Image (cartoon, coloured by chain):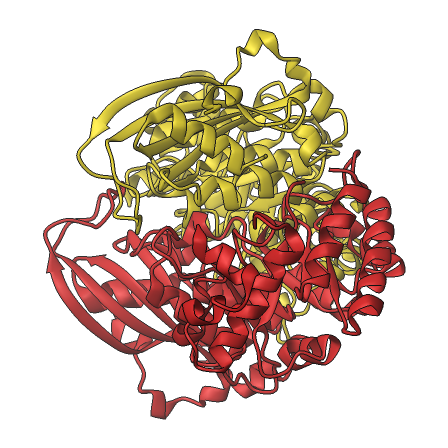
Chain colours: A red, B yellow
Amino acid sequence: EDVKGFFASRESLDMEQYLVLDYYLESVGDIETALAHFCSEQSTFRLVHAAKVIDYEVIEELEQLSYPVKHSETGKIHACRVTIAHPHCNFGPKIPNLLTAVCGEGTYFTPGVPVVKLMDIHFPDTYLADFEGPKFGIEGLRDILNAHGRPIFFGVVKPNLSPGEFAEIAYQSWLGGLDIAKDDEMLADVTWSSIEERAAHLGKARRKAEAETGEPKIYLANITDEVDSLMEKHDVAVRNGANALLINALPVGLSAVRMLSNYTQVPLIGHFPFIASFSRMEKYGIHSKVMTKLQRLAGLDAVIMPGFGDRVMTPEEEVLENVIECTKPMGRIKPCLPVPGGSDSALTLQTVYEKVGNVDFGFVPGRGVFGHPMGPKAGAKSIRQAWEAIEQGISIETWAETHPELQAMVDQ
Amino acid sequence: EDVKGFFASRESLDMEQYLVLDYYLESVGDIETALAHFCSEQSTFRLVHAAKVIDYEVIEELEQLSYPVKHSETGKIHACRVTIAHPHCNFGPKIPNLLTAVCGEGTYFTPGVPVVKLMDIHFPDTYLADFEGPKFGIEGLRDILNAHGRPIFFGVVKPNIGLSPGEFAEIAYQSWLGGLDIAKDDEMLADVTWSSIEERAAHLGKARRKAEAETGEPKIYLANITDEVDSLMEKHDVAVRNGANALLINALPVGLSAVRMLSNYTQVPLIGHFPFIASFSRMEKYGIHSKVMTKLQRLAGLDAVIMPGFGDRVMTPEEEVLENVIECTKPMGRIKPCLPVPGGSDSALTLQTVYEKVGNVDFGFVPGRGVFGHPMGPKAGAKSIRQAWEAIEQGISIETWAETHPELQAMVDQ
C-alpha cells in the first residue's frame, strides 16, 4: 500500500528523462494520497514510467472548491501548488501525445482532485533536441524587414471587401511606414475573397510599396483551413506575394502547425482564437503561457496574443509571462516574436515598450491607423512619429507639436 | 446607434444560410448593446456577413459575475441565454474556420461580455451536405461484430502501460474468449520505443484472429494511433496491415481537422477518446459545452465516441452525459449516427442502470472493474458481463441470475 512510490527528490532522478510540470490543484481528503492518485492517473508504479511528485506547497485550507464540481469525495479541501516529474519516454517528441499525458483524462478526472490548472511546462535539452522550432524567429523576421532596434509594426486592414479595395488600404499603410499588413483571423478562403484573388492584388501592392519606400514590406495572409489543405494554401499564397502566413494555432491544432512549419518557405505567425475557453479561469484549465510555449515549440515565428490595457480581459502579469515564453532561452529553439495586441495606438506605444523592457515585440494599433482622420497612410505615419519621439526621449505631446499626423491623434 | 441591425426574426432569414448557436453569457451594461457588440465581434453590419440575435432570454440580474474575470466595464450584470444566427458563408465547411468564428477571439473578448459558454450548435442540411461524417457509424460497427440487439462490450486491457506486446496479447485474448467485443489500447499508449505500433499490432492481430476461430464470433482489436498529424496515415497502414480492425484517436489533442482527414482515408472504424475536452467544458457557465465537441467529433467522422459516463464518482453531471449520448445518435442530416460509449464506474453490476438511463441498446459499455481484476481472471470477468446482459434480457435480476452463474456470483460477492 504505497503512496510514497510516487514521490521522489529531483536529485534522485535523471532529469534529462523527465518533463517538469507545475499544477495548481484542489485536493479532497489526505493530500499525499490525492497527489499519488494524480500521478498514477496520468501515467501508470513502474520506476521508468511513473510520473513523480518532486515538490509541493499547501497554500491554504478551503471551506469549498473554487468552482462547483460534481464529486462524491469526502474530506478536507486544500489548495496546492505541485511540481511533477513526468518521464517523456511515455509520449515522445509528439505534440498530441504530450497533450494527452499532461492535460488529458488523468489530469482532470482523478478522484479527489476536481479542480486543476496546468501552470507551466519545462522541457530538458534532451527532449527539445527532437524538435525543430521556428525556422525564422525574431531575427529571421527582422532580416526580412531590415527592421533593427525598433518594434515591428502590424496593421490589421479594416474593413473585411474585394481584393482590390483591401489592396489600396494596405498600400497606404505600408507607404506611411507599417511593416506588416494582415488579414483578419476570421478572413481566410471564401467566396467573395479567395486566397488566390486576395494574394495576387496584395502581392502587387506590396512590391509597389517596397519600390516607392525603398524598404521591405510584409503581406501576412491568413491560410487557416482544413489540415489537408494547408500546404496548397501556402503554395498559392506565396506564389502570389504573401511573404508571411497567419494560422489560427488551436483551431488547426498544434501538430498541424508543426507540419506547416517544416514545409513553409516563409515565416508563420499564430493567432489566439479558442485559447480563452480553457485559460480564463484563474484556478482551472491551462495557463495561456503553456500554449504560447507550445506554439513556439511547434514552430511559429511570431505569436499574436492579448496585450496591455484596462479593456483587455487578461491580467497584465499574465501578458508579461507570455511575452517572456516567446523570447527566453529554450535549448536551441529560436525565439519567436511576441505580438501583444491591446487597446493600442500611437499614444500607447511608450507604455508597451516600457512594460516589455526591450524592442523585441510587434505592436498592433487597434485604432488610429486605419481610423486616423487623415487616412491609413497618416495613421501609419503617426505610429512611426511616436516611435521616433520615444527614441529621442521626447514626450509624444512635444513631438506632435512639429508633426501634424501625430498631433491629429493627440487631438482625439 | 444600430444595435438593432444585429437583431432579426428567424422568419425574416433564409435559415439554410445560417448556423444556429446557443450561448449562455453574462453581460455588463445595456443588454441589447452588449449583444450587438457580441454579434459584431464574431463577424462584422452587412446583410450577408453579420451574425444576428434571433432570440434571447434575460435569466436574472446578478450582483457579481459567476467567475472574477479582469474587466474594465461597469454597469448592471445580467445572466442571459442567447440564440444567434451565424451565416456560414463566413467560414465554409471547414472545421478550423468554424471554431475560429463561434468560439474564437470575438466569442471570449467582447467588451462587456466577460463570461460566455457556447451551449449548442444546430447545422442546417445545406451546411451538412459538404461533410462526410462517419464512414461506418453504429450500424457499420454492429455489422463488423455481428452484434445486434445488445450493447457493444469494450475492455481496456490492463495493466495499461509498460507491458510487452506479447504480455498484452494473452490478456486481450482471454477477454475476447470470455465474450468481449473490443479490446483496446490505453489512450496514453500509442507508438513508443518499448511498445511500437508494429510489434503490438502483429501480436494483438494474431490473438484476435485466433479468438475469432476459437469463439466463432468476430472480434475487434482497437489500436491507439494518436501521433503527429503527418504520421497518422502511415500508422493507420501499419496497424491495419497487422490486424487492428479499428483505430483509436485522441480527438482534441490531434485536432478535429486531422480526425476529418484520417476519417476520409481510413479503411476501418475510428473511435474518439476524450482527453483535453474537460479543460474548457467543466465550468458550468464558461467555455464550451461537452455536447458540442461530441457533435463535432461525429461531424468530423468518428464512428464511436468514448465519453465520461454514469456513476457518482464521475465528475460530469448525469444530465450532461445523457445530452452527449443523444448527440451521437440523433438525426443530423445524412450524417451517420456514431456509437456513444459512456465510460463510468462500471461493472456487470451497473449494466442494467446504464441500459435503463440510455433507453435502448445503442451504446458501448466499458467496465472499469471486475473484468481484468475479476477474481477468476480476464476470461471470467468478460463472462460475468455477458451473464449480466442475459439476465437483463430475461428480465431477471442480477442476483437471481448469479445463483446459477458462478462468474457473475463472484462479482456480487466482492
Task: Please state if B29 lies on the left or on the right of B191 as rendered.
Answer: left
- Tell me, yes or no, if residue A223 can be seen here: yes
Task: Please state if B178 lies on the left or on the right of A279 as rendered.
Answer: right
Q: Looking at the picture, how far across and down is residue A314, in whole percent?
A: 37, 56
Residue at the location (28% across, 38% down)? B312
Task: Please state if A214 lies on the left or on the right of B125 as rendered.
Answer: right
Quarter location, residue B296: top right
Residue closest to the far right: A239
Which is more toward the observer, A123 or B396? A123
Q: Looking at the picture, how far across and down is residue B291, in whole percent?
A: 48, 33
Q: Is residue A301 above or below residue A146?
A: above
Q: Looking at the picture, how far across and down is residue B140, in whole percent?
A: 72, 30
Residue at the location (62% across, 31% down)? B338
Residue at the location (61% across, 63% down)? A381
Which is more toward the observer, B403 or B100? B100
On-image quarter of the N terminus of chain A: bottom left
Q: Looking at the picture, how far across and down is residue A181, in whole percent?
A: 69, 58
Q: Is residue B308 above or below residue B189?
A: above
Residue closest to the far top: B11
Residue at the location (20% across, 62% down)? A79
